[PDB]
Length: 49
Length: 48
Length: 49
Ligand SMILES: *[C@@H]1O[C@H](CO)[C@@H](O[C@@H]2O[C@H](CO)[C@@H](O)[C@H](O)[C@H]2NC(C)=O)[C@H](O)[C@H]1NC(C)=O
Image (tube, rainbow over all chains, first blue to last red; front, side):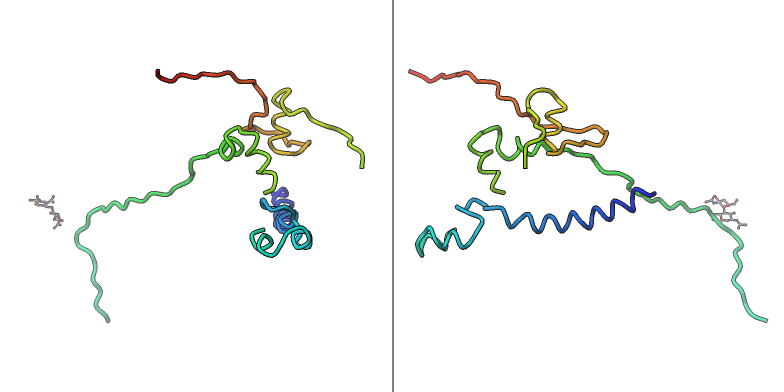
């Protein structure tokens, strides 16, 4: 009955870490950063990445 | 006074009811499900 | 910043557990695991003349 007090604290924190970790994924693009896609490609290839 | 309808005969009636207590437990091998053991697929899955 | 410990993920089954759940502390239980072994293949070719 005490292990459910900690499992709510852990559930609160696991939701926030799955938000911040989806910003370092590239999802198959050349980079996870928009300022690098805009600096390496041209205007018709930027829109696909 | 008042009128009251009181029983003079009876039966026993049976009500049935199902309550579900469990489901089937399933574990999935995620690597074999997605990439089927191909190394070219497994390097593309690191981007997700 | 230094690598303190490593796990070869194809050595035994505790290593497959640690690499399948991606943690070093594993919290006593019964777990289903994935395969990380190489197992070099052969060839079976059969076509008609
Ligand atoms: C209460 O109702 C039941 C059923 O309506 C009565 O049982 C019947 O009794 C008669 C005479 O004994 C039989 O011929 C029938 O076959 C019975 N029916 C059934 C379904 O068993 C019962 O007599 C009633 N009780 C009173 C006090 O009226």
